[PDB]
Image (cartoon, grey):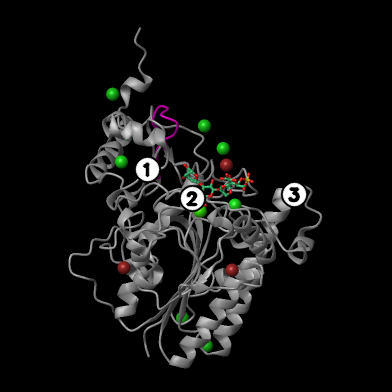
């Protein structure tokens, strides 16, 4: 039929300069590069939050996490009891469910991080099939983590880390035997073949945990980078390379089943690279978690041979929030009544090279221990507050590294963008959970969120003398 298949390939903590098509000089990603070159590379792509849980929530709900109560990560080994509601609210309908109701065969593979209790399970949230783990990460070698899991059960460990838990397949044990990146690639191939056999459009949410810690890589991938002297960089490159291998096999499967031409492949990272653990975000400033560009500006391409031209670069800013309305539009799917969305259906803009966010803002706000980091972009201009320092105004097109603070030269533009961003925060909800005890103390006493203090300007720079 006319409706395209959709494959999201979502990496975890992949740095900005860590794929070939986005600038890498040491990591080799020929299969991803080939896809990017045969479609549209997005040079100003943003995720809705600079860390996983809230970013993933935003991709699947189509709303900023500040509107859904999900702006902090779930903790390690979060409650698996429905009564504790440790998960994204069930009332916020996921794009997977919408696609499933419109006749797609739907599959999620890899990392979830959206709730470990039954009501939050992928199979309850629109996925016909799920293969992966429910929490925030996982050790990569089954021979290693299955030994550790059994050994800790035998020792009577009452709090085994979910990183070594057996993975699952629709709620049954997975009995994985491969390096799990290779396993996730295998399950993607299989689900592509199932969709081909059913003669049904597919939506596959392939959430590799690579290159997220722990840095663990196959010897055969390491040898591709054996000369790289920094052991972290060497292992990380091999981890990314393994994803690239899997994408190459997925691509051959799509061609063999004749689904390649009419499949939209979207590749991105859930957030910026963590430069403490192998990642490189050049030329951006900062690291995973920041509201510098480095925390939430990510590599992205769209690949869809039927519609998207080759060698395209799309330079206008876009959001991972656009995936929900764009995909449901492509699926000719009807949104549930009352569903709220923060992004736009951008596919016509990509095809015509027009500006979807013209005179509109793409935002980040990240909660810290007593203050807020903020970023906000319109057109060529961005405002940033990091570490509760004085506000910065950057021409992000001219100054991608956020080095030249123009707040003094153009104070009206600064204040203009502040006012719009402060108005945005008036729609926020309270978090359903926070992350640390410190967090809970600050919110309970009203020290957080204090958006009013976040949007102070002149008193941060004026001298009292
Ligand atoms: O690894 S060891 O040093 O041996 O200790 C481990 C374990 O420590 C790890 O926990 C996580 C897995 O690797 C890193 C180690 O510190 C951690 O990475 C974290 O993964 C999370 C997802 O599972 C998140 O990505 C997390 O990042 C977040 O951190 C906070 C919360 O939200 C923001 C930020 O505010 C986000 O960036 C990331 O750091 C240790 O916990 C355990 O005690 O011992 C193990 C060894 O047995
Ligand atoms: Br749902
Ligand atoms: Br397993
Ligand atoms: Br860290
Ligand atoms: Ca991440
Ligand atoms: Cl453990
Ligand atoms: Cl084809
Ligand atoms: Cl740091
Ligand atoms: Cl064409
Ligand atoms: Cl700085
Ligand atoms: Cl001005
Ligand atoms: Cl709270
Ligand atoms: Cl002020």
| Residue bearing mark 2 | 76
Q: Nearer the viewer, residue 464 or 174?
A: 174
Tag of residue 434: 1
| Residue bearing mark 3 | 231
| For marks 3 and 1 on the same chain, the one whose residue lies earlier in the sequence | 3
Q: Position of residue 51 (x, y in %)?
A: 46, 49
Decide if ligand 12 comes within 8 Å of the CB at mark 1.
yes
SS for callout 1: loop
Query: Where are the magenta residues, as a range?
Result: 381-393
In the visual, does 377 lie left or right of 419? right
SS for callout 2: loop
Is there any visible trace of residue 133 in the rendered image?
yes
Magenta-drawn stretch contains 91? no
- In the displayed structure, 405 sits above or below 133; it is above
Residue appearing at x 50%, y 41% in the figure? 399
Q: Nearer the viewer, residue 22 or 225?
A: 225
């Amino acid at each position: 039929e006319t409706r395209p298949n959709i494959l999201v390939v979502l990496c975890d903590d992949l740095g900005y300069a860590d794929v070939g098509f986005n600038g890498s000089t040491d990591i080799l990603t020929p299969e991803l590069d080939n896809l990017a070159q045969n479609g549209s590379i997005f040079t100003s792509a943003y995720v809705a939050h600079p860390f996983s849980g809230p970013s993933r929530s935003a991709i699947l709900t189509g709303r900023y996490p500040h509107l859904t109560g999900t702006a902090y990560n779930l903790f390690h080994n979060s409650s698996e009891d429905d009564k504790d509601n440790m998960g994204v609210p069930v009332e916020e309908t996921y794009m997977s469910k919408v696609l499933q109701n419109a006749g797609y065969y739907t599959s999620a593979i890899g990392k979830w991080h959206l709730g470990a209790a039954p009501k939050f399970h992928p199979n309850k949230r629109g996925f016909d099939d799920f293969y992966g783990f429910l929490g925030g990460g996982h050790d990569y070698f089954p021979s290693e983590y299955q030994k550790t899991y059994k050994a800790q059960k035998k020792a009577g460990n009452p709090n085994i880390r979910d990183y070594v838990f057996p993975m699952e397949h629709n709620g049954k044990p997975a009995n994985e035997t491969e390096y799990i990146t290779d396993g996730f690639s295998r399950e993607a191939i299989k689900n592509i073949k199932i969709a081909a056999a059913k003669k049904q459009p597919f939506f596959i949410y392939l959430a590799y945990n690579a290159p997220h810690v722990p840095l663990q890589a196959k010897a055969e991938d390491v040898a591709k980078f054996a000369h790289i002297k920094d052991k972290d960089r060497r292992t990380y490159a091999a981890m990314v390379y393994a994803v690239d291998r899997g994408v190459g096999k997925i691509v051959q499967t799509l061609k063999e089943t004749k689904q390649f031409d009419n499949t939209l492949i979207v590749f991105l990272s859930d957030n910026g690279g963590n430069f403490n653990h192998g990642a490189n975000n050049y030329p951006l400033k900062g690291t995973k978690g920041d509201t510098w560009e480095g925390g939430y500006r990510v590599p992205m391409f769209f690949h869809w041979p039927k519609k998207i031209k080759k060698d395209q670069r799309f330079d206008f800013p876009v959001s991972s929030l656009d995936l929900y309305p764009t995909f449901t539009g492509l699926a000719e799917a009807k949104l549930p009544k009352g569903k709220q969305l923060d992004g736009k259906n951008i596919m016509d803009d990509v095809l015509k090279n027009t500006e979807p966010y013209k005179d509109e803002m793409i935002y980040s706000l990240r909660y810290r221990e007593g203050y807020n980091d903020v970023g906000a972009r319109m057109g060529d201009w961005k405002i940033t507050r990091m570490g509760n320092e004085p506000w910065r105004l950057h021409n992000i097109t001219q100054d991608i590294g956020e080095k030249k603070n123009l707040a003094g030269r153009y104070p009206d533009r600064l204040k203009e963008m502040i006012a719009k961003t402060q108005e945005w925060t008036k729609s926020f909800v309270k978090p359903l959970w926070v992350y640390s005890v410190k967090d809970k103390e600050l919110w309970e006493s009203g020290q957080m969120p204090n958006y009013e203090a976040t949007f102070e300007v002149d008193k941060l720079v004026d001298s009292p003398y």
